Amino acid sequence: MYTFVVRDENSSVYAEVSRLLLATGQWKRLRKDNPRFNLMLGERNRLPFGRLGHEPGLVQLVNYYRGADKLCRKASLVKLIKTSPELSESCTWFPESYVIYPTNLTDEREVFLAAYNRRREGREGNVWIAKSSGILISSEASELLDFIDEQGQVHVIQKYLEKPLLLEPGHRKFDIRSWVLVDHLYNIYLYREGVLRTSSEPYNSANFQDKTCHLTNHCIQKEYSKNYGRYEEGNEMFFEEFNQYLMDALNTTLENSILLQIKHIIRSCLMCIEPAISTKHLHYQSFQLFGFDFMVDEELKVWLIEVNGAPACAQKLYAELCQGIVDVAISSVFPLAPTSIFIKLHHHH
Amino acid sequence: MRECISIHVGQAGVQIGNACWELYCLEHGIQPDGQMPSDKTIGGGDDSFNTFFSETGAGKHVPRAVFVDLEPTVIDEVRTGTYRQLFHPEQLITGKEDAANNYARGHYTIGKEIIDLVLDRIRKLADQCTGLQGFLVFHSFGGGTGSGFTSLLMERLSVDYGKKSKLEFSIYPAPQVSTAVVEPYNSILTTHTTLEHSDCAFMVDNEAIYDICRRNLDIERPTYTNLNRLISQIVSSITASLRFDGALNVDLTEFQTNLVPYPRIHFPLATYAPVISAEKAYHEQLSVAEITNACFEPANQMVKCDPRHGKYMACCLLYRGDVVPKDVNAAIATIKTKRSIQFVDWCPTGFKVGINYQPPTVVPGGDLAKVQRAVCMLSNTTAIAEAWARLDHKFDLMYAKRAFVHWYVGEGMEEGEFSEAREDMAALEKDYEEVGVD
Amino acid sequence: MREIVHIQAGQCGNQIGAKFWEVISDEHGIDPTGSYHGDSDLQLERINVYYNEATGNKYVPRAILVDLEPGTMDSVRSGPFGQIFRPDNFVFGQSGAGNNWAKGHYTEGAELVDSVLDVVRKESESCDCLQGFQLTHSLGGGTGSGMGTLLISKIREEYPDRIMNTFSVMPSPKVSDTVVEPYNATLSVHQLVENTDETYCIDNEALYDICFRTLKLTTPTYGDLNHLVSATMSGVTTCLRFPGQLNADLRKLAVNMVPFPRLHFFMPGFAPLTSRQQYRALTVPELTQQMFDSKNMMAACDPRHGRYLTVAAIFRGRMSMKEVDEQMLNVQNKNSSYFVEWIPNNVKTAVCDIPPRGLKMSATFIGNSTAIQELFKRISEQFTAMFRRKAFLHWYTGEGMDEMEFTEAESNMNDLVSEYQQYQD
Amino acid sequence: MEVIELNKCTSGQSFEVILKPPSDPSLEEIQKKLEAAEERRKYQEAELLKHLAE
Ligand SMILES: Nc1nc2c(ncn2[C@@H]2O[C@H](COP(=O)(O)OP(=O)(O)OP(=O)(O)O)[C@@H](O)[C@H]2O)c(=O)[nH]1
Ligand SMILES: Nc1ncnc2c1ncn2[C@@H]1O[C@H](COP(=O)(O)OP(=O)(O)CP(=O)(O)O)[C@@H](O)[C@H]1O
Ligand SMILES: Nc1nc2c(ncn2[C@@H]2O[C@H](COP(=O)(O)OP(=O)(O)O)[C@@H](O)[C@H]2O)c(=O)[nH]1
Ligand SMILES: CS(=O)(=O)N1CCN(Cc2ccco2)CC1
Ligand SMILES: [Ca+2]
Ligand SMILES: [Ca+2]
Ligand SMILES: [Ca+2]
Ligand SMILES: [Mg+2]
Ligand SMILES: [Mg+2]
Ligand SMILES: [Mg+2]
């Protein structure tokens, strides 16, 4: 009989994972403060990694890689790409970004303005975006820096994709969410199912004020947009439909024009930090589900927007994925008495 | 030459001490009777081995040690063991009844009635020293004498020997070989009252030694003998610089300077490699790089914890055997490119290297196999504070219900000394976090 | 040299004490005359914990025999190892106690207690370093119950910093001598709560059920009940009588088992327990599954009705110490909802190389469980069913007692039950 | 990668490599504490005896 504890009640993912575990009859949940556990569904912030792997007889497993925040933080991600030779500052799949500390607190204010005055001088598109861990889109550098000083937390300004790939009909923006699971062996598995969180408003490049056609967030489209649910159900187009579209319209497949780059980007990021977060020779073991967000330009080039370390899942895919998390992440470490739903990304450990 | 007095307190301290002086003698060519053939100066001399061994006119090399236990059954083994002839009886101090795993009993009730006797015996060793450096104190955290009496001793030593240094070898409680439920209480109590009196302390977690013994030596259920012969190999590596010719860590003062830039943060992490089973058919000898790289694997750290997710304040490599500086730097360069080594901004990113050409001595019939070269890394990581976190957690669980507190109050200790000690650890954990995280 | 002084009082005390001394005398190689004839140095390593060494290499148990009538002790003197006890340690009267707690504690007993302490003091003065005492007695009778607690109160006065340990036979209506046993048990339990550091609660119904159901004895007897108590007493004391690390000391066992002063009442257990398919070897997994089985416990309480504050397990024999750790961890990890989460690692395991007589290996269980409150409720309930009608009180008031005292003992134990209740949640 | 302070002797050598530069209670007070706790033990035992006297 395997045992587990739950330290994140707000997790829709591992809530269903806990539902499936008990459904097997071979798992038993414990109070969130019981140290004798096989598996910890730990909290988001301040997970006590230092108390793991010190229970004699109990092999202990947790669903969070200690140190992955370096990859799942706006300012941390940028700092990781500009400093890691494996990614290099010349990384071609990550928008030109800079870390900007508000003036009420290193900081890349001057480095950002240099590349700005260059673009503004070369007649080139000089639209940028500012965000943090409240977003502002503007073409003038004065409005971006003034917006961060009004706050009190670190911000990041990166190039805004002026030429996104729009779905027809609708002339609308979108972003692709791919779920990636890394197990204790550090095998990289890509869930065969993705989701396109699409905008129901025609993309308008001459007005970055109305952030309804530029931001594809599932909450902003369902709160500030007026065409929500028009084309696809809940502004969520799955890989089956999006693939058929790329064929009829563009005469290519989601595999060739987009997925190859997505799998290349997922490999480069995770293989990069492997020496820092791997639990190969650790007294405890780690796995973690990641949520990658990508953009696509009219040239069918993929760009990395951010990585989410505690992502939620599309309503239509909670069963398949959660059952998959148990097969490859939990049963592979605590077996029970296909056609895998994942795409292994082999690499040189 | 400046002498070093070693003090062994409680069962753990005594047994570990007994296993180190066995190794010291084997290393310096001293026999069980105290004779030393290679020592060509009879009855004196200021050699490097003299920092740990005094000499008699008859040629006996006597350890500059004192063994103190509130119960005689453990020190009685020393009096009749292989090395019974090394010590004279004044060095072996024993009481009648122990502290019963009660910090307050060792510190107050029983400690008060024997502290003046220990000091007197230590004074006799001091009077033999022309230039005393300090003391090395071996004790356990969880034991009642090892915790309660050691803190009382450390207080008086700071009073009677002000300008002297004191280093600790401390055994961290591990349930797999622990015989007490209240060891978290004792560990935190003794850290609170000792913190301002210890200049540098090496914490060995029994959990780490225990699993090294099961993994590397294929011992299914390790005994204290197994645990101690391994601990004395590491301790020998840390104390070698004091007992042999050299220019690094030559005296006790240099440990604080090289390893402790801030007083409260004086708990360096120790890693050791290679540990090979003597029962093995025959092992392929590891290289300088291979054993250096092994210093960054948690599996051979004296306390399990992830230095990758901390920050270094000082790193020190101690090699024994066939090692030349060129090979060491060749390995460091390689490891810097493949490992996560993050120092603090106010420290140099470097390593102080010491090499001793004599390879590790192995006790005949022991568990370890003879190797051509071995290294012991002393690094001051913020990651070692994970051990504080683990310990403080268990404290909070029991103290929140006042469990077992009545045993301590019954010995004269006030309940507020618990919260007073726990608040100190709260400050210790915060210090590590201020230094390690961004 | 950590000496323990033994005291057995009353009919039950002396009959169980005698068998105890009969069982461990065999383990340490001592014959009925006190001559050692063992084959292992481990038998003598800690022999002086319970035995004194006289002239001629004779070993005399450090035990004092007490009672208010001569009958039971006359038998011990005639029993198998009766000749091995020190003649001067037989202290007895002639009146008896009539199963009356007040007679053993206030009238008949007071007349004889001073001469018992004269013997205890004489045994203590000869100890290099006395740990504490252990008393064997029943709580339902008059001497072991009334005078027994009286002795403890006076021992704690003359040795206030020594450990007081008792094996207490709790009364049960199913295995009863008289109807006043709940009266005598309630009065003693208050003295024990106040003046002992460890008390092994042995319920006579548990002993009965184990002989009838498990051992398959068609008609149990006190003699059969005392066999179990002997084996259990031998087991719970293995830590003291042989070389070891855990609970090898009276005070150390208290420090590890008693998180709160008043909650020092233990449930003992023993394994194996087999009827006569007796030669079958017992595997470590089996040995552990039984030791934790309620049917192998002798407090007649259900552990799954409370929670374990602490536990002390002792495995005897030549076995896989690695396989023991595995099974002990499997028990705690497969049923971790019956251990308190605010005492980490509250289960300690000890090993002994010497097995009990006639067994390749065995395990003894010592549990500090909040479930023991079920025992104190049985006694309390039976007490109130009589005291509410003041039934049988005249036996006691005739010895100078007032009803107020009964009302206090009743309140004192209901408090004890409430104390156990706040820690079960 | 710089080597500094190389010291060589017959039984070994030691050096330093820099990859990168940076960016009590008196005797009186102890005796009182030892006697303070002893005073709280005497008190606790007197109450025990006082109790046993009643
Ligand atoms: N590594 C190692 N640990 C030991 C050894 N002996 C005891 N310990 C540990 O020390 C802790 C108990 O403290 P002890 O040193 O035995 O107790 P003490 O200092 O003698 O004080 P008392 O309570 O009076 O016995 C337990 O966690 C043991 O695991 C030993 O020889 N080697
Ligand atoms: N450089 C850029 N170019 C184009 N669009 C961008 C962009 N940066 C952000 N966006 C838009 O912002 C949205 C994502 O914002 P972001 O992910 O930074 O905030 P967030 O992290 O709170 C949402 P999530 O739930 O995916 O984490 C996407 O829909 C994308 O269209
Ligand atoms: N297990 C066991 N219990 C006994 C024995 N003799 C008496 N008892 C129990 O002890 C209680 C009677 O006390 P008893 O010892 O006879 O009175 P005392 O001689 O005045 O102390 C009753 O509850 C009996 O069940 C015995 O030999 N074995
Ligand atoms: C011989 S008897 O008089 O029939 N008998 C009556 C019950 N009593 C108590 C008892 C029952 C089982 C064991 O002990 C023992 C003596
Ligand atoms: Ca000399
Ligand atoms: Ca000082
Ligand atoms: Ca009379
Ligand atoms: Mg986000
Ligand atoms: Mg001890
Ligand atoms: Mg009777």
Image (cartoon, rainbow, N blue to C red):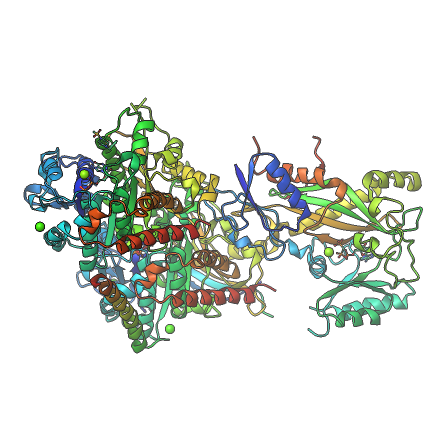
Q: Viewed as shown, does residue B287 lie left or right of C236?
A: right
Compared to residue B204, the image places residue A286 above or below, namely: above
Q: Is residue B30 visible?
A: no
Residue C176 x %, y %: 26, 36
Q: How many labels were placed on the picture? A: 0
- Residue B438 is drawn in which quadrant? bottom right
Residue at point 27%, 62% (across, down): B65
Instruction: Determine the quadrant in which ligand 4 lies.
Output: top left
Residue at far top of view: C277
Residue at point 86%, 57% (across, down): A212
Residue at point 33%, 70% (across, down): B155
Q: Is residue C7 visible?
A: yes
Q: Nearer the viewer, residue B387 or C213?
A: C213
Q: Nearer the viewer, residue B334 or C169?
A: C169
Q: Viewed as shown, does residue C98 lie left or right of C300?
A: left
Residue C293 x %, y %: 39, 35
Residue at far left of view: C56
- Residue A156 is drawn in which quadrant? bottom right
Residue B44 x %, y %: 23, 66
Name the quarter where the C terminus of chain A is drawn. top right
Q: Viewed as shown, does residue A323 lie left or right of A40?
A: right
Q: Nearer the viewer, residue B267 or A155?
A: A155
Residue A16 x %, y %: 66, 42
- Residue C402 is drawn in which quadrant? bottom left
